[PDB]
Image (spheres, rainbow, N blue to C red):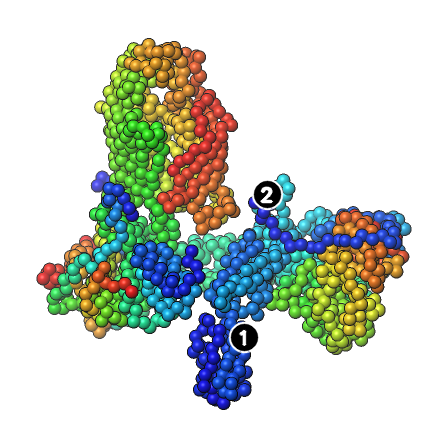
């Protein structure tokens, strides 16, 4: 497919297939580029273009290894601001990719895993590159993500309420209470533990919740 | 309703009459933690108040419950033992 | 992909995690205070100038 | 001598500095003649160096290097049975791959290890040949040739030390086959060492359950018979001189459940000892304590084997643990669906004791989900108190939904298309959806079936269904029969147990008909309705809006909900008409769901499928004929055409048909053939007995990555549908169905290829017993 | 599929069927279907011109070797036990001395039938069947059993004199280390390649010497007809180890005079200084005793299924498990005769003695051969 060419002759055609939007061959060029020249001078920049070609072709299992490969090539880079975003971005596409949105159905209760794995990377990013342009974006991803977990965990804390499992209600909320200071899912789990307490005759603790209910409706 | 079939529901996290004898007011949470372990609830914004609370639905024959709240002080030295059944 | 009545031309790509707003903090009263974050939510709350979503670069 | 410049010739994978620092004399260093020789082997110590020849011009080093870097390809030839990646795993075991340093010293060494792989795999008579084929600018192809003579096969095992049982009956327990006849093939005979290891334990069990408590395998030596085929074994054991279970001496943390333990150690003193029973009996306590809250019920027994009397005494040491191990539960792999669907499919509550029975039932609740691939969890005892276990249900889902398609009438014609779609577990909500219907020039059918399985939290499985069949039997729009049929029926989930559940529902059905055919049993129904029209004209209309109470009940014991292995699911369904209906009748039916694993590998599973159905009037009336039972053509019997097994219709002479298209649709029509004739169309019976005999079989030609998705099963599918109210007086030149003995048959093999949208089932069958004839399509292609 | 699924490496055929000295049989008197393609170490006896031959099926014969007419016949195919209706199932070859037909059975129950009638003059259940010939000399039945033990058993009644493990490989690495009574020492080879001299009279190790490094990290053969039974010329053992590594080594210390580790030799006879041997490719060679300096070879026999080479009619005679016999020009290699007396072939060996050549073919057992 991609034969023995000069590396730039591979790379410009890879840049062509990137600018053609043909990530399929742009993956196929850049691999045999770094197969023929892993000692390529831009073999690191092959990977950044590869994850570019992976993600635009939606190729996270290739983008999983390459982000680890870029670390395993050299874990120190100026390009981690791409990569640590792109790993969270990989986890963002790994979080949810289904089509249920136009059905009036949301995906914020499905995967906490690559949610938190993105929340791992995006927090590492705003740790590792608070200077890079991604930090405006990645923080807003993190802003979105905690409530996405909260709504997910609210949907968990919903079920034990609809189950009536009030002991299983509380600690699910007690997680969110020691997780989220701002999320409205926590603000709306806030009345229910009071109820769960009053179903558990912990009315006294529930009026102590009802203060916070008053205080966080304030 | 008029349906004798209702499925049973249980909760867990309670203690025995031997277990409530295993501690006294004045004892540590650790002394509860040695004899009874911890329960699966305490008072998070307030003092050490350990909750061995049971809930149970039999199946359209009543509802069953046993609440055991164990208020220590902040030091974890026990200050209150309150057993509470259903209703 | 391609089409002739064209409601297929909406293909992948979004900034969904960018679109919302942040949320409203805790104002719990005295004595009813419990710790609010134990998770990984202790992030460095900062930005790095703009360039968000599709405006974010791809190197 | 201090080198001014080192000349780095032919490195090609390593850097100059990766060459330079590995030289024990670097540039600018004092050069020694030992350091010349040190530059030889340390550069050779890369393994990428084919030559190192270190010279200088006075002091300025010139290191003449040829290079053995990257293998650029690895080619296999002759491995045809075995996967050559398993062979490549031995290269990965030797640190060798494509893009890895060539080392021609390691050719025969790994070649040995592939033949040592062959030595271990059950061959020894198998050679390999790595052929180094040099590729551009440093590179090499690992062409690999494999010269496989023969594997080793089981021949005969000597057993010594057995002195009560047969050698031969011991082999009958085993994996160890050394016979496949010229007129029998049940499998193969080949060797593997790990078969023997369990067959030690198969033997080790086999004496232990008798009583043999001084039983011990002395040694076991496989003959290295000099033929490269002969697998002969001496296995040396000590017999054991069987001992009695004379008593149980349980001890330790009995946790107050000690009487239950005594029920769990209800034993016989003097019983000829069975440690496998004890192997069971200890875990019954661990299952007892697994429901009594204790997740680490440490039970360490001790058989005080008393050789003075040939008895054992059974010390048991119990350590229960914590009473409330269940903290909470984690649920993962929900990345498509809703977890509250899965979390309502559990029976363990958080903040509880360990109930082990609550776990696996909830796992069985996910087993009877049928929209999954792995049911699996991690009972993580959280570090801290042993009140903390968080049980982590990382599970794998499966494809939902199915379309089915059976279109005809050409692509170039008018309004005609067949449809049908399912989205059971709609969008992770669990909503059981299946929707069909058609717009045809023969009908306009509408159909819906949606279910909230949990409209109440118990599992009120609120399922709504409706239909609208505006059928016309297209001669003009009429003239065979007009029939608009429509109505609805909603039925909910009624838990009789957690494996038993009832159904009960009410069916609205309006049918509106005109120009019906003069023919006997259709009109025999009408005469049972007291309606006796003109028997030579289709000048007849009929309007019915029947109201019926429907019901059902499900026994639910089969393992998976999509791919089970064992059990039985008895799913009763039936109906009765109510007052206000336009006809007073009923129908009752039942089809079974029984799996019979041939071996308890559950690889071959017999699928016992028979079907029952009976429909009748409620006294003085009749069940109508459209719900008479129909069969054949992948119904319960394959290889026929659809709904072709049953009683067959007898037509009156039509002298009016309201239209005839000049001798077309001939059913004794108004033009031609107008006589009392019998159609080969199956009119169907008021009673049904059809069955299908299915037997799961694996196939070696499929990878079991996806052979476990594909179910292959032969059959001999027979059945009878018959009319218990059939007569000989109305049917005298016409055959009879008053007898139940109306049995057709068609036989073949079934297959499902589980596509990315699930099984798309194809079926061939061929009739070898046919009761009075039907219509046949021997190959059938379904979904 | 299965016409294309096959894979078998090649074994060279038999060329050169010669009949320069017209070979015959003396007679056939065959016991029956003998060992067959079943593997055991059975081999008949011909003492006092009596063919003590049997089959591993169970029929035992004594054949008066003139047409091999029967002297006596018994059947140690037994009838009941923890297995009922026993066959013979013999592990050790037919040894006869005294009124005792010493045979090792795969039952690990060994016998000594009164040679006048074949009634069991004594018998013994022993620790494992014999992996070698019942070596019977000096009051002692010298056994290399399955367990690698030097099982010494009294030949007069079946009293175990001792039982001492020499060489225990990873599995039954099948070596025929028949413990040779040689010059007062228990001289025995190895199923590993570790060779040894032990005391004959008590089982006291004179020495034990490693020669062949066994398969598993030093991989060796499982087709070769390796005589791991030793041969001593009084001070020097001239023997093969477990793969066929030929070694001249001292009787009393085990110290190597010379060794052909290059040999993976199948069979051998030390004929003076002309060790007439069967090479590993089922071809012929012959080396010295003064070094392993090769005298000659032959590869007309090549990849055949051979028995031992014997000296009959002044000729190097050899048979094979394809049922041929063959007559090597004893020094100069050449086929002089070829008697394909059967096709059943031989797992026992030719016995170029009593003026005859005793074999037990696999199915047509006893042919007595002449030319």
**Residue sitting nearer the eye, D524 or D359:** D524
Residue E355, visible in the rendered structure: yes
Q: Is residue D190 above or below residue E310?
A: above
Instruction: Check the residue under mark 2 and report the chain it is in.
Output: D
The residue that disc 2 covers is D185
Would you say E192 lies left or right of D367 here?
right
Q: What's the residue at 64%, 55% (across, down)? A: E9
How far from the left and from the top, in percent, is residue D264? 44, 54
Q: Which mark is residue D51?
A: 1
**Residue sitting nearer the eye, E189 or A6:** A6
Q: What's the residue at 41%, 11% (across, down)? A: D729
Q: Is mark 1 on a helix, strand or loop?
A: loop
How far from the left and from the top, in percent, is residue D200? 57, 57
Q: Is mark 2 on a helix, strand or loop?
A: loop
Residue D717, visible in the rendered structure: no
Would you say D292 lies left or right of E279 here?
left
Q: Is residue D653 above or below residue D487?
A: above
Mark 1, other Cα within 10 Å: few <14 / some 14–19 / many ≥20: some
Task: Tell me how many marks there are.
Answer: 2
How far from the left and from the top, in percent, is residue D24? 48, 83
Q: Which mark is residue B24?
A: none
Quadrant hosting residue A139: bottom left
Q: In this view, does D207 lie above or below D757?
A: below
**Residue sitting nearer the eye, E48 or A27:** A27
Quadrant hosting residue E335: bottom right
**Considering only order in the chain, which callout, 1 or 2, is on the residue closer to the N terminus?**
1
Quadrant hosting residue E298: bottom right
Q: In this view, does E184 lie above or below D768?
A: below
Would you say D255 lies left or right of D103 here?
left
Q: What's the residue at 86%, 50% (across, down)? A: E25
């Amino acid at each position: 497919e991609v034969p023995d060419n000069p590396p730039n002759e591979i790379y410009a055609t890879a840049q062509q297939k990137l600018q053609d939007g043909n990530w399929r061959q742009a993956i196929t060029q850049l691999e045999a580029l770094d197969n023929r020249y892993p000692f390529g001078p831009y073999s690191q920049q092959v990977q950044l273009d590869l994850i570019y070609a992976y993600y635009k072709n939606a190729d996270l299992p290739l983008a999983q290894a390459a982000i680890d490969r870029f670390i395993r090539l050299n874990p120190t880079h100026p390009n981690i601001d791409y990569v640590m975003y792109m790993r969270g971005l990989t986890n963002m596409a790994l979080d949810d990719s289904a089509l249920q949105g136009f059905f009036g159905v949301d995906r914020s209760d499905r995967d906490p895993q690559h949610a938190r794995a993105a929340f791992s990377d995006f927090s590492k990013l705003v740790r590792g590159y608070p200077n890079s342009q991604y930090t405006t974006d990645a923080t807003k991803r993190l802003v979105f993500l905690k409530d996405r977990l909260a709504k997910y965990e609210y949907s968990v804390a919903e079920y034990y309420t609809e189950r009536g499992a009030w002991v299983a209600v509380v600690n699910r909320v007690e997680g969110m209470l020691r997780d989220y200071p701002d999320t409205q899912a926590t603000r709306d789990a806030l009345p229910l533990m009071e109820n769960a307490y009053r179903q558990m005759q912990m009315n006294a603790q529930a009026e102590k919740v009802a203060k916070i209910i008053a205080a966080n409706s304030s | 309703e008029r349906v004798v079939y209702r499925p049973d529901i249980n909760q867990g996290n309670y203690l025995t009459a031997n277990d409530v004898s295993k501690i006294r007011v004045g004892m540590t949470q650790q002394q509860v933690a040695y004899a009874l372990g911890t329960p699966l609830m305490s008072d998070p914004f307030g003092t050490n108040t350990w909750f061995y609370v049971f809930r149970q639905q039999p199946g359209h024959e009543g509802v069953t419950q046993q609440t055991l709240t164990l208020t220590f002080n902040s030091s974890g030295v026990l200050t209150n033992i309150d057993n509470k059944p259903a209703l | 992909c391609s089409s002739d009545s064209r409601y297929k031309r909406q293909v992948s790509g979004d900034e969904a995690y960018l679109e919302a707003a942040p949320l409203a903090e805790l104002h719990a009263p005295a004595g009813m205070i419990l710790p609010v974050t134990s998770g990984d939510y202790a992030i460095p709350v900062t930005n790095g100038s703009g360039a968000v979503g599709k405006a974010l670069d791809i190197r | 001598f201090v080198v001014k410049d080192i000349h780095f010739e032919g490195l090609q994978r390593v850097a100059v500095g990766a060459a330079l620092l590995s030289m024990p004399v670097r540039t600018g260093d004092t050069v020694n003649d030992e350091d010349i020789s040190n530059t030889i082997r340390a550069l050779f110590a890369t393994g990428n160096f084919e030559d190192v020849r270190v010279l200088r011009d006075g002091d300025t080093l010139l290191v003449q290097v040829k290079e053995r870097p990257t293998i650029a390809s690895i080619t296999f030839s002759g491995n045809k049975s075995v996967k050559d990646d398993m062979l490549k795993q031995n290269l990965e075991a030797s640190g060798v791959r494509v893009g890895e340093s060539l080392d021609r010293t390691t050719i025969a060494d790994i070649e040995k290890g592939l033949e040592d792989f062959y030595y271990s795999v059950g061959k020894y008579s198998a050679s390999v040949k790595a052929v180094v084929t040099p590729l551009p600018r440093n590179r090499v192809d690992l062409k690999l040739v494999f010269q496989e003579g023969v594997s080793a096969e089981i021949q005969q095992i000597n057993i010594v030390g057995n002195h009560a049982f047969t050698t031969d009956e011991l082999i009958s327990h085993f994996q160890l086959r050394d016979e496949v006849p010229w007129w029998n093939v049940v499998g193969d005979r080949k060797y593997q060492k790990q078969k023997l290891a369990g067959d030690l334990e198969t033997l080790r069990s086999y004496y232990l359950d008798r009583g043999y408590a001084r039983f011990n395998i002395d040694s076991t030596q496989v003959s290295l018979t000099p033929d490269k085929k002969g697998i002969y074994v001496t296995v040396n054991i000590t017999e054991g001189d069987q001992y009695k279970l004379s008593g149980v001496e349980v001890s330790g943390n009995l946790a107050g459940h000690s009487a239950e333990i005594e029920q769990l150690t209800k034993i016989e003193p003097g019983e000829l000892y069975n440690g496998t029973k004890v192997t069971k009996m200890e875990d019954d306590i661990k299952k007892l304590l697994g429901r009594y809250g204790y997740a680490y019920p440490r039970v360490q027994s001790m058989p005080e084997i008393n050789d003075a009397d040939k008895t054992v005494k059974l010390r048991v040491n119990v350590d229960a643990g914590n009473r409330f191990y269940v903290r909470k539960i984690r649920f993962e792999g929900n990345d498509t669906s809703k977890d509250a669907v899965l979390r309502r499919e559990m029976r363990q509550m958080e903040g509880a004791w360990l109930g082990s029975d609550l776990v696996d039932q909830g796992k069985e609740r996910l087993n009877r989900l049928g929209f999954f691939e792995t049911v699996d969890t991690d009972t993580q005892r959280v570090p801290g108190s042993p009140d903390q276990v968080d049980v982590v249900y990382k599970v794998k889902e499966r494809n939902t939904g199915s379309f089915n398609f059976g279109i005809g009438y050409g692509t170039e014609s008018g309004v005609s298309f067949q449809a049908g779609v399912q989205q059971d577990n709609w969008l992770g909500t669990g909503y059981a959806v299946g929707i069909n219907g058609t717009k045809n020039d023969y009908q306009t059918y509408a159909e819906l079936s949606v279910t909230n399985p949990y409209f109440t939290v118990d599992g009120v499985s609120l399922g709504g269904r409706l239909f609208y069949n505006d059928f016309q039997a297209d001669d003009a729009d009429l003239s065979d029969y007009t029939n608009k049929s429509y109505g609805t029926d909603v039925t909910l989930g009624f838990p009789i147990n957690e494996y038993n559940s009832l159904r009960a529902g009410l069916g609205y059905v309006h049918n509106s008909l005109s120009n019906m055919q003069p023919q006997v049993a259709m009109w025999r129904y009408l005469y049972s309705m007291g309606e006796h029209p003109s028997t030579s004209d289709q000048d007849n209309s009929f309007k019915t809006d029947d109201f019926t109470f429907n019901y059902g009940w499900t026994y639910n014991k089969l393992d998976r909900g999509y791919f089970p292995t064992d059990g039985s699911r008895v799913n009763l369904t039936g109906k009765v008409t109510i007052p206000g209906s336009d006809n007073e009748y009923y129908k009752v039916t039942l089809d079974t769901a029984t799996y019979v694993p041939i071996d308890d590998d559950h690889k071959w599973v017999v699928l016992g499928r028979t079907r029952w159905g009976y429909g009748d009037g409620l006294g003085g009336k009749e069940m109508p004929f459209y719900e008479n039972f129909y069969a054949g053509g992948s119904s319960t019997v394959r290889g026929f055409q659809s709904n072709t097994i049953g009683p067959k219709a007898v037509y009156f002479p039509h002298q009016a048909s309201n239209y005839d298209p000049d001798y077309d649709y001939e059913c004794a029509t108004q033009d031609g053939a107008k006589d009392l004739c019998k159609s080969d169309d199956a009119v169907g019976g008021n009673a049904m007995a059809v069955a299908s005999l299915e037997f799961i079989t694996p196939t070696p030609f499929i990878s079991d990555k996806y052979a476990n998705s594909v179910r292959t099963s032969f059959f001999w599918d027979m059945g009878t549908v018959w009319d218990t109210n059939w007569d000989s007086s109305q049917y005298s030149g016409y055959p009879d169905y008053s007898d139940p003995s109306n049995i057709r048959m068609s036989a073949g093999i079934a297959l499902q290829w589980m596509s990315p949208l699930g099984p798309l089932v194809f079926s061939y069958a061929q009739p070898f017993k046919k009761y009075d004839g039907d219509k046949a399509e021997q190959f059938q292609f379904n979904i | 599929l299965f016409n294309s699924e096959e894979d078998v490496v090649k074994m060279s055929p038999l060329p050169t069927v010669e009949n320069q000295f017209t070979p015959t049989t003396a007679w056939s008197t065959s016991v029956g279907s003998g060992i067959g393609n079943f593997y055991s170490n059975l081999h008949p006896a011909l003492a006092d011109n009596v063919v003590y031959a049997a089959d591993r099926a169970g029929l035992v014969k004594a054949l008066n070797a003139d047409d091999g007419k029967e002297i006596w016949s018994v059947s140690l195919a037994e009838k009941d036990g923890w297995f009922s209706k026993e066959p013979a199932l013999l592990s050790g070859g037919v040894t006869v001395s005294g009124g005792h037909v010493y045979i090792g059975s795969e039952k690990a129950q060994v016998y000594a039938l009164n040679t006048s009638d074949g009634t069991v003059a004594w018998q013994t259940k022993v620790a494992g069947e014999a992996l070698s010939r019942p070596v019977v000399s000096d009051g002692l039945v010298l056994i290399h059993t399955s367990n690698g033990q030097l099982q010494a058993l009294n030949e007069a009644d079946g009293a175990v004199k001792w039982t001492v493990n020499l060489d225990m490989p990873s599995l039954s690495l099948r070596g025929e280390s028949a413990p040779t009574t040689a010059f007062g020492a228990a001289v025995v080879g190895g199923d590993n390649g570790r060779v040894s001299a032990v005391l004959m009279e008590q089982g006291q190790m004179i020495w034990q010497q490693r020669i062949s490094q066994a398969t598993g990290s030093t991989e060796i053969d499982r087709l070769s007809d390796v005589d791991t039974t030793p041969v001593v010329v009084n001070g020097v053992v001239f023997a093969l180890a477990y793969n066929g590594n030929l070694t001249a080594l001292d009787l009393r210390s085990g110290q190597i005079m010379w060794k052909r580790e290059l040999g993976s030799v199948n069979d051998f006879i030390v004929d003076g200084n002309r060790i007439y041997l069967v090479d590993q490719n089922d071809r012929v060679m012959a080396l010295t005793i003064d070094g392993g300096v090769t005298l000659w070879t032959q590869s007309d026999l090549l990849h055949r299924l051979l028995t031992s080479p014997v000296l009959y009619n002044g000729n190097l005679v050899v048979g094979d498990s394809e049922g041929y016999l063959h007559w090597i020009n004893v020094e100069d290699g050449r086929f002089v005769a070829q008697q394909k007396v059967d096709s059943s072939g031989f797992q026992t060996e030719p016995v170029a003695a009593d003026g005859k050549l005793l074999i037990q073919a696999k199915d047509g057992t006893v042919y007595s051969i002449t030319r």
